[PDB]
Image 1 (cartoon, each protein chain N blue to C red):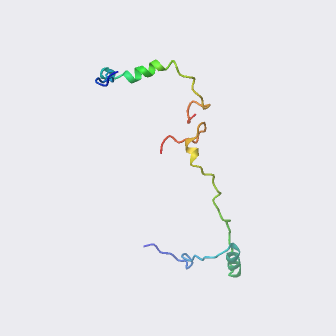
Image 2: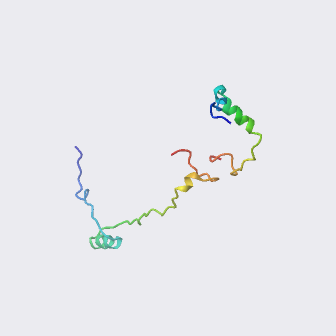
Image 3: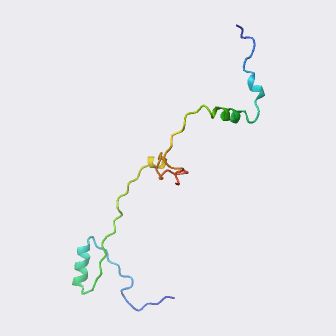
Length: 43
Length: 62
């Protein structure tokens, strides 16, 4: 146990597509989405 | 300029009811045509309908 060092260093190597890469990775864990019955409010 | 030859071109009379106007026209000898009042029918307005979950009334902008 020590408070001398900073442990939030992983965010120093985040590229431009890190957020969307993580979203693509997470896409396989989600539940199926509900459907309103139409493709669009203009349908 | 614009000339006219009849004297009743600017004559507009105001009445409270249709029956009163009919009586005036009848006693003054004029032949009349009457049109019934056009009242706008009540509407069904709803602000929430702009954000419907599955209905076409949902708006795409504000």
